[PDB]
Length: 140
Length: 140
Ligand SMILES: Cc1cc2nc3c(=O)[nH]c(=O)nc-3n(C[C@H](O)[C@H](O)[C@H](O)COP(=O)(O)O)c2cc1C
Ligand SMILES: [Cl-]
Image (cartoon, rainbow over all chains, first blue to last red):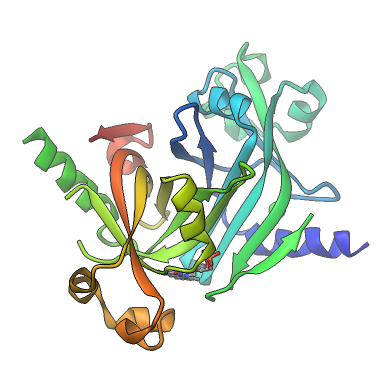
C-alpha cells in the first residue's frame, strides 16, 4: 500500500523530535497543550502511544472530547508537523509491556505496578507538515 | 501587580522563541495546528494572517485557541490558552510589521488580504528548567 509509504513518511518527519505538544479541548471549549514524548516508533498502524497516569488532568479532557492534535516543532530541522486524530485512554496490559522502558521509572516509580499507569493512544487521521506556507498533507 | 509580574514571566518565557504552533477547532470538532510567527513584544499575542484563511473561518465559529511554544535548547515548553479575534486595524499592522514576515506576506502591508489575529490570553501553562519541568500556571 501507499499506506506503508505514508506511515514511512510520517516516521521520517517526526523520528528525531522527542517531545510534541499534545492539545485537547475541554468542556468550556478551551484548548490546553501538554508536552508529551511518545513510546515506540510508528509502524503499520498509524497510531501514536503515550504513557500517562490515568488521573492526569488531560485524561478527563480526552475522555470527553476524543479529537486531539499533536504538533511537532523542529527549528533544528526547519520542520513543523500537525497531527490530527482521535485519542483514547486504554490500560492495555500487552501494549504497556511492549512499550515499557526502564527510563520511565523516574515518572513511574513502581513501573508497571503503578496502580494508575495507563496509555493514551492517538489514531492518526490527517497530517499536515511544513518542510513552507501551505502544508503538505497526508491522509490516513 | 502580581499581574504585571506574570506578564513579565510570560515575556521571559517566549521572547526568544520565533514560531509557535497555533491550534484551532473546526466545525467537525477536529483540531488543526499551524506554525505562526509571533509579532510584537498586555496579556495579548499578535499574528499576521490572511482574512480569507481557513483558520479565520475556524476562529470565527470557535474563538478559543491554543498557541504552543517549544524550545528544547532553552529547556521550556509553553501552552497559551486564549481567545482569538480577527483585527483589520491598519495602524496596528504598521506598528507590528517586521521585514521577516515578507516570506509569508510578499507584498507586505500592501497584500490585499492581510490582517491580524489578536489572541487574548486566558491561561499560560509552562514546563521549564526553573520549574524542574513540573507544570506551572499563570491565569489572567
Ligand atoms: C515557520 C512558518 C511560519 C509561518 N507564519 C505564518 C504567519 O505568521 N501567518 C500565516 O497566515 N501563515 C503562516 N505560516 C503558514 C500557516 O502555517 C498556514 O499554513 C497558512 O496560514 C494557511 O493556513 P489556513 O488553513 O488557515 O489557510 C507559516 C508557515 C511556516 C512554516
Ligand atoms: Cl516514529
